Image (cartoon, rainbow, N blue to C red):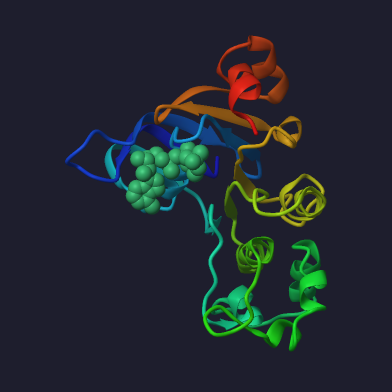
Amino acid sequence: NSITVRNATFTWARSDPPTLNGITFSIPEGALVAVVGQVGCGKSSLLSALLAEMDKVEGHVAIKGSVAYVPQQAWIQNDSLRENILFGCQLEEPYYRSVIQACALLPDLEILPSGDRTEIGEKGVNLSGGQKQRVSLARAVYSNADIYLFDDPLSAVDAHVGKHIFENVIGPKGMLKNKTRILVTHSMSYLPQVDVIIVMSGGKISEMGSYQELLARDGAFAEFLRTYAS
Ligand SMILES: Nc1ncnc2c1ncn2[C@@H]1O[C@H](COP(=O)(O)OP(=O)(O)OP(=O)(O)O)[C@@H](O)[C@H]1O
Ligand SMILES: [Mg+2]
């Protein structure tokens, strides 16, 4: 297991009840695992907890290897698009080329005045929400971590681009097919294709299993599909 969490409780503020309570799960190395649940149920917080960005009140957390993150709202550094991807790393080919292609960046680069050397962020070219998201994906993919935490990574891109990113970056035929990948998503579109789904409610885990297992149970996952998925 690349991730092992045992009866773990995490807080953003000791003055109030913890946001995440009694979290217990293990993720096999190389698994693709979705995390779903009603808006506000604690999905982003779960990723923050794994990044050691919350305060662990109690419990056990063991994470094997490096961790990359694609946050829920993409952000841009004041620098070239290239440096927004490299983010401290040296540029290496053909890996860089593969990341550009996989993250659907070619159509964006093609209309930029200096391609990837274009200054983006403050006082530079004004990227769209979809463009920022593709840059954010590329930043994480380029770092070539062992574990990927994706916070609703297809929300800001259109359906066609989303399909490209799932196929080339996230899924079993993508370039990260050997990595552990945790996929928070509000969408049902790719849930049949993940290995395991973790359903959350109220800062706790309600149930875990495959798409087919959870669907048949007609419990929390079935309710997510009927009422919350969008
Ligand atoms: N970076 C942060 N700093 C402080 N509090 C946070 C942070 N991120 C989330 N929270 C808090 O955690 C609680 C659960 O919200 P969280 O954002 O984890 O839910 P979510 O399931 O990701 O919601 P959504 O479906 O809207 O993305 C909320 O009180 C929220 O304000
Ligand atoms: Mg969230």
Residue 177, position in %: x, y?
Answer: 74, 50
> Residue 81 sits in which quadrant?
bottom right
Residue 118, position in %: x, y?
Answer: 67, 85
Query: In the image, is residue 119 above or below residue 198?
Result: below
Residue 185, position in %: x, y?
Answer: 61, 40
- Could you tell whether 184 is left or right of 159 in the image? left
Query: In the image, is residue 47 above or below residue 204?
Result: below
Whether residue 214 appears in this view of the structure is: yes
Query: In the image, is residue 169 above or below residue 44?
Result: below
Query: In the image, is residue 89 above or below residue 10?
Result: below
> 108 or 62, which is in the foreground?
108
- Could you tell whether 41 is left or right of 188 in the image? left
Image point (55%, 78%), residue name: 121
Quadrant location, the C terminus: top right
Quadrant location, the N terminus: top right
Image point (47%, 46%), residue name: 47
